[PDB]
Image (cartoon, each protein chain N blue to C red):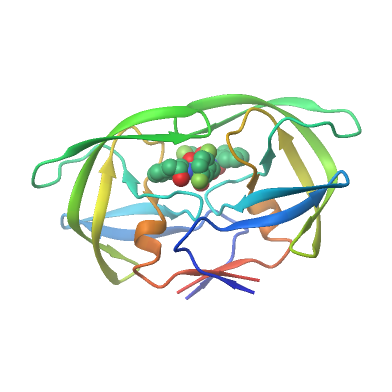
Length: 99
Length: 99
Ligand SMILES: O=C(N[C@H]1c2ccccc2C[C@H]1O)[C@H](OCc1cc(F)ccc1F)[C@H](O)[C@@H](O)[C@@H](OCc1cc(F)ccc1F)C(=O)N[C@H]1c2ccccc2C[C@H]1O
């Protein structure tokens, strides 16, 4: 589809068998979701944005469905104020910026 | 133009007769640039990101050229890690997300 930017570009995603709301964020290098339980081992990481850095748990090889599209990639979990779908997964669904 | 997201969506902008690099960020509600001098009076604003909040200066009716497209709107100035072009200006240039 084609998404306008008059409002925040929020979409529904399916992960770990759960439906959540997330933001399509071209300014985010990676994908970060609010605290939740995911399978497998994880690695600690620090990510920075406006305001500073936060510590997150890094999980690799996670399957996510974005608007009916299946994508696989690294997913970070931590105290983010909103669920963020970053570039690492946006590329997999063939998302582009156009004007 | 059509921009893929395999790399950061950086473009050249022109403001105050100077060329700068900025990120096209659909996840940012507003446009914020690194410390610089702009004309007129400013008002205070607080913006929150992934790591907390930062105080910025708000300037209105500022001319800014993005990838050749002229836009006139609100620009925030403050301790941002990178120059960010937010939805307020992305909509002025007709930018949309597609997949
Ligand atoms: O921190 C960032 N990337 C980092 C990131 C994020 C997730 C995972 C990894 C990485 C690392 C880095 O890319 C991005 O900023 C630029 C940025 C880019 C970069 F390239 C390096 C450092 C940077 F600061 C960030 O994802 C923004 O896309 C956006 O974050 C999601 C979000 C959306 C909301 F609607 C509300 C709250 C919220 F938090 C955000 O902070 N929006 C707020 C904002 C911004 C400017 C003006 C006003 C307002 C109010 C909000 O909209």
